[PDB]
Image (cartoon, grey):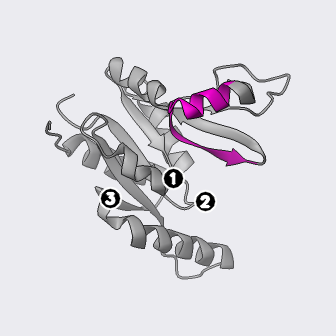
Amino acid sequence: FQGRKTLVLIGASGVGRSHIKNALLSQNPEKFVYPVPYTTRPPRKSEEDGKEYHFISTEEMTRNISANEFLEFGSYQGNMFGTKFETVHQIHKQNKIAILDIEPQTLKIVRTAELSPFIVFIAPTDQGTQTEALQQLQKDSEAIRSQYAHYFDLSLVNNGVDETLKKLQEAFDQACSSPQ
């Protein structure tokens, strides 16, 4: 670590942020790790504890939340989800880069020297022929960019995953971090 320790991706839902993250992990599995989240969702018979999620009770989750153990947590379809501080710390302990796909309001919390984040905004491509779906995504994206611009180290348009990755890793690798 002579540079940034954590890659933070911000964007409206539907921009392809998840594809970017998965492509990075798939391409450099020894460098990047995505912290496995916690959920109160009852697992299905088929799922493996600690693969896509750590499955806990609402009682444990509640204790964790009030113990300030979550960098981020929230409710989806009536179940609780969150990412623990400690899961990101364990990645940095192994000298790997944490990839965090967080919500914009969590930006106030991650911008620290300890986490040394490189914060990348991912925008949709401005395509000429527009669906109403692209138009809404562009509006959602501009709403987030407008409020949180001062947080971003880099704004990129998603012009395809392999092309976005190349630009993204180069900008990441070039980034400086200093202590204090």
Q: CA distance from mark 1 to mark 2?
A: 13 Å
| Residue drawn at (54%, 62%) of the image | 12
Label 2 sits on a secondary structure element that is loop
The part of the image, by quadrant, that contains residue 51 is top right
Instruction: Quadrant for residue 172, please give it.
Output: top left
Magenta residue check for 73: yes
- The residue pinned by badge 3 equals 151
Query: Which amino acid is tagged 2?
Result: Gly
Report the side of 101 relative to 135 (left or right). left
Q: Earlier in the sequence, mark 1 or mark 3?
A: 1
- Of residues 16 and 75, which is closer to you in this image? 75
In the rendered structure, which amino acid carries the disc numbered 1? Glu
Q: Is residue 64 left or right of residue 161?
A: right
Residue 13, position in %: x, y?
Answer: 59, 59
Amino acid carrying label 3: it is: Tyr
Q: Secondary structure at mark 3?
A: helix
Q: Which residues are magenta?
A: 60-76
Q: Which residue is mark 2?
A: 14
